[PDB]
Image (cartoon, rainbow over all chains, first blue to last red; front, side, top):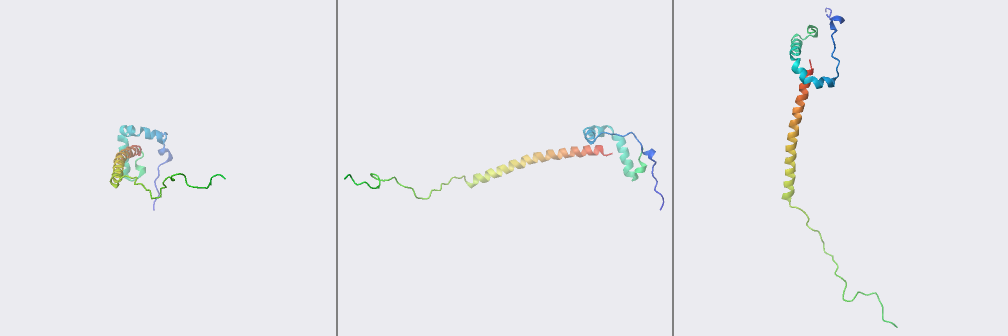
Length: 57
Length: 71
């Protein structure tokens, strides 16, 4: 029934945010205030496409 | 040939001895106890109201932190 398309391992690499959960919780309110626009763009893409392979950028 | 000496009651008489039932009343009225209980209940209700509303606000704050972190 057709092959499944998958991104290459090179396409999945990105600079990683490597702080623990407590750091994120401490900074969460200001992070949601400051980085709102790209996060909302990503969530809209995610909930409209219904496919994680289309919202990687 | 001295006087007769025998175990006997003392001159005049022995002191009166109690025998009747003695159970004092020793209590508050029912109205006072009911009033104290109802007052305690109302005070507890109001304190719990304040604390539960504060806890609801705290839960909302934590949920908002999770929402911020989700993307």
